[PDB]
Image 1 (cartoon, rainbow, N blue to C red):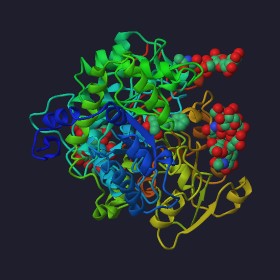
Image 2 (tube, rainbow, N blue to C red; image 1 turned 45 degrees about the vertical axis):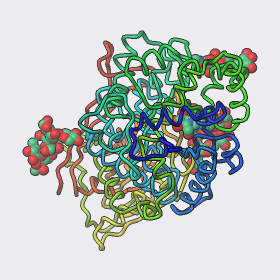
Image 3 (cartoon, rainbow, N blue to C red; image 1 turned 180 degrees about the horizontal axis):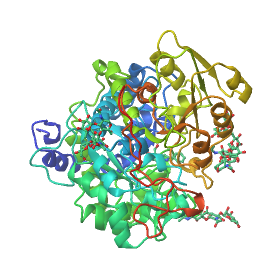
Length: 602
Ligand SMILES: *[C@@H]1O[C@H](CO)[C@@H](O[C@@H]2O[C@H](CO)[C@@H](O[C@@H]3O[C@H](CO[C@H]4O[C@H](CO)[C@@H](O)[C@H](O)[C@@H]4O[C@@H]4O[C@H](CO)[C@@H](O)[C@H](O)[C@H]4NC(C)=O)[C@@H](O)[C@H](O)[C@@H]3O[C@@H]3OC[C@@H](O)[C@H](O)[C@H]3O)[C@H](O)[C@H]2NC(C)=O)[C@H](O[C@@H]2O[C@@H](C)[C@@H](O)[C@@H](O)[C@@H]2O)[C@H]1NC(C)=O
Ligand SMILES: *[C@@H]1O[C@H](CO)[C@@H](O[C@@H]2O[C@H](CO)[C@@H](O[C@@H]3O[C@H](CO)[C@@H](O)[C@H](O)[C@@H]3O[C@@H]3OC[C@@H](O)[C@H](O)[C@H]3O)[C@H](O)[C@H]2NC(C)=O)[C@H](O[C@@H]2O[C@@H](C)[C@@H](O)[C@@H](O)[C@@H]2O)[C@H]1NC(C)=O
Ligand SMILES: *[C@@H]1O[C@H](CO)[C@@H](O[C@@H]2O[C@H](CO)[C@@H](O[C@@H]3O[C@H](CO)[C@@H](O)[C@H](O)[C@@H]3O)[C@H](O)[C@H]2NC(C)=O)[C@H](O)[C@H]1NC(C)=O
Ligand SMILES: OC[C@@H]1[C@@H](O)[C@H](O)[C@@H](O)c2nc(-c3ccccc3)cn21
């Protein structure tokens, strides 16, 4: 017979229905199953008709693996999936959340909070475009981004993954989506999924919904807010995502007024699917269904029932697929979960796969490998890093000479601090490892390296990680650049009730600035206690987590470009004020949202 679903000339909806009508229950449940590459094998993928794989943070074929190595890995998995009776290609997902960040040599862009500081949605679109190319360079078709959380309390470990505490800024930055996926057609119906083809990736608006509104910024916790507030703060950017054809939505670990998002049929089915008319696929977070219960995983039968009935389509298991498949099969065999629900989930998954061209181009393009770390993308990251910087102070009194921009020609200068020559620290979490890491973890340019690359050949650059006061006073320095701040973190490991930077940091700034005029570069995922750093410093720059291209920092320090970044978040006076956001009745910031000093290019 002619087999319609294999015909690339046929409409997506026709292809979906034709394929769905041929599938066994095992093949359907297989599509709904996403597994870690760490548990995948050719036989496993074939035997269980697996629909998707992912790499979690740090889940890589080997350290320092080339783009070709990633392609060969993904293709090996694909070959197994293509060998099934129906030959449904798998989709491979990864957290490419500031570039293709798990991958050695990938361009690392500034994290979201810094991007928010740029107020430049077209810049963010261009980052999406570059990111899609670097993800496809590694054979991967699906990025778990953007995080469109609206972080309402910086004690949250994922505050850096949020563009802003102001939903309007988060809404504007949804331009990442058509960057990653391609621009939607003129005819486009809001809520339909879209990916332009083999040089773009499926995107993922996450985490639905209110992940940024949890009590005291406790990760995965309870968001206590009325429906009006949920809809006014936490929801708006999802509608922009629908308008831009986001292919997938990932559900949050968090709860809304005590109801787990992973079990919330009202929001997932009633609102996202039935009201916003979302027609792509809904994916769980990692063991997100396990975490419906207390303790997590204590009633996995319930977890599967609750989540699938709530409206989730694909489960990021990611390890215990046999248990998942067995339990879901049993619920269906028993009539507890209707075939209509399974058919809906599979319809949505297949719709995304056919739409994005996956059946036509299931394998990697070796000619794309060279896109990884491409200099043009690094130039873009450098632009973004520079634009993200917020100048908080530029002179100790209203009558001092402005310190910035600094002269490129001086007899001798000092570069100091724990963050001056630490690529891992300047990238933060979700870089190479899940939690990020310390030192030279990838290809990039540290602040020290950037200074050396910028200054006149006659200027002597001295590096001292933690010099004492006497070293500085006796050094004959013209000025110093001192870089300090937070260590890399991700998710719960980043939750922090005190928001004070690790030492040595302040002590180094005090030692250096006490001896010579100093520009302090603060590397952080969020506002942190800053008055003492301010008091010591002639100038102070909030650089956020600027990524691999440290020359973005020096581009502004030395006046190649003027500072333009503006705070995308409130800077608090103390943590006991928190939560405190723009528009609050009680609003007493150290620096308001939108604050930022400027300079002009030399
Ligand atoms: C304000 O709250 C913060 C969050 O609660 C808190 O930071 C956390 O402190 C705890 C300890 O109280 C840390 O847990 C331990 O981490 C040890 C190793 O920590 C180093 O490596 C990790 C990455 O693996 C970094 O994230 C850390 O920052 C730290 O980095 C090292 O720091 C040195 C000093 O600056 C540097 O010289 C050094 O170069 C640098 N090294 C690296 C690799 O960058 C582990 O060995 C411990 O076992 C412990 O781990 C925990 O074990 C219990 C388990 O429940 C936890 O899940 C597990 O994490 C934690 O890492 C840290 N969180 C961060 C930074 O994200 C602040 O504490 C301050 O900083 C810490 C690091 C200590 O210096 C404290 O003495 C200090 O108080 C809180 N600040 C205040 C004022 O109270
Ligand atoms: C010395 O520095 C100052 C301060 O940065 C420069 O003035 C700024 O110039 C910006 C760029 O031209 C102005 O931004 C624009 O503002 C308009 C009006 O709101 C807006 O419609 C534009 O989109 C743009 O806004 C930016 O868009 C990109 C975002 O990422 C960014 O966050 C937005 O700010 C800005 O308003 C202006 N600021 C002030 C206080 O005047 C100044 O530049 C000089 O003057 C401006 C007005 C303009 O005519 C420039 O061509 C001109 O160079 C700069 N001076 C020099 C000599 O470089
Ligand atoms: C929001 O976060 C709080 C704080 O982490 C969560 O409450 C905590 O819930 C855990 C279990 O999920 C409790 O752990 C248990 O502690 C008791 C101690 O008697 C012990 O018997 C158990 O073995 C287990 O370890 C923990 O006590 C509790 N913490 C506090 C201080 O209340 C809360 O569940 C989170 N809410 C949401 C919606 O996620
Ligand atoms: O990496 C896959 C997803 C990612 O896309 C989500 O944004 C994020 O919430 C997340 N946390 C874990 C994860 C959490 C705890 C242990 C192991 C893994 C896994 N993931």
